[PDB]
Image (cartoon, rainbow, N blue to C red; front, side):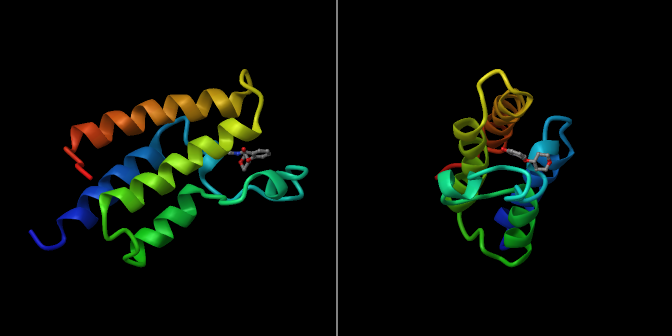
Length: 108
Ligand SMILES: CNC(=O)c1ccccc1OC1CCOCC1
């Protein structure tokens, strides 16, 4: 009853991380891999960083969690071409994410 949010968030983040379309998002994009990524994307985010944030008790509300995870998708979509494998992954996983958020009644 106290630590309810933490539990729900952890379950959701784990399901997202195990999803077969999560692989592009598991770790920070490297500048060496992506020319001018960090010029274009000002608030980078990824699921390893979110795991850390969660463990660090940063996600004190649904909204903070939802914003970080939404940003993972919107970074990817802005940066990559629309028919790229990363873009396809991003919308697949975003669909999955919204279905789990609704499924847990996460209200913000
Ligand atoms: C979400 N990822 C990207 O927008 C990305 C863009 C350009 C180059 C690499 C990228 O991320 C890699 C991070 C490590 O796994 C493979 C994708």
